[PDB]
């Protein structure tokens, strides 16, 4: 079921950017295919241009990895819409915690 406010994002990820990190999960996805949207520091606010999400699949991808040395937990806001044409967004706060890279 789509119910998990907290999320995890690796740091110092190396490979091919932009790169995907984790899928998103809302809630209204129990009545109609809901699409996503993102806004807040990391997307539109400084640092602007870091995280990006697919309003269709809800895949959370980023152009820049995270850094525990800088921030241990990032926070973003998102909106929801019905792939049918009806808006179903709501002030949703997504919490993204940082986790040790695959290196350990």
Image (cartoon, rainbow, N blue to C red):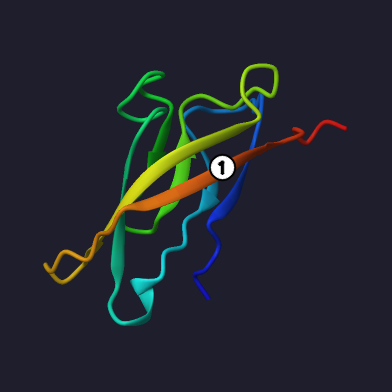
Rendered view: 3 above or below 63: below
User: Where residue 53 sits in the image (x, y, percent)?
Assistant: 38, 45
- Number of residues whose C-alpha sits closer than 10 Å to that of mark 1, classed few (under 14), some (14–19) or many (20 or more): some
Rendered view: 72 above or below 92: above
Outermost residue toward the left? 85
Residue 4, given in percent of the width and then of the height, sits at: 55, 62
Q: Residue at x 47, y 56 (%)?
A: 24
Does the rendering let one see residue 74? yes
Does residue 55 appear in this view? no
Q: Quadrant of the C terminus?
A: top right
Residue 54 picture location, percent across and down: 35, 49
Looking at this view, is 12 or 47 the one in front? Answer: 47
- At a point 21% along the width and 67% down the height, the residue shown is 83
**Residue where numbered disc 1 is placed:** 96
Residue at 46% of width from left, 46% of height from top? 60
- List x then y, in percent, for residue 34: 30, 67
Which of the 4 quarters of the picture holds residue 57? bottom left
């Amino acid at each position: 079921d789509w119910v998990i406010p907290p999320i995890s994002c690796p740091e110092n990820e190396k490979g091919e950017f932009p790169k995907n990190l984790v899928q998103i999960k809302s809630n209204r996805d129990k009545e109609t295919k809901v699409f996503y949207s993102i806004t807040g520091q990391g997307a539109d606010k400084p640092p602007v241009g870091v995280f990006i999400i697919e309003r269709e699949t809800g895949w959370l991808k980023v152009t820049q990895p995270l850094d525990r040395e800088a921030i241990a937990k990032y926070i973003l806001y998102s909106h929801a819409v019905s792939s049918n044409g009806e808006a179903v967004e709501d002030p949703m706060e997504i919490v993204i915690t940082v986790t040790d890279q695959n290196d350990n």
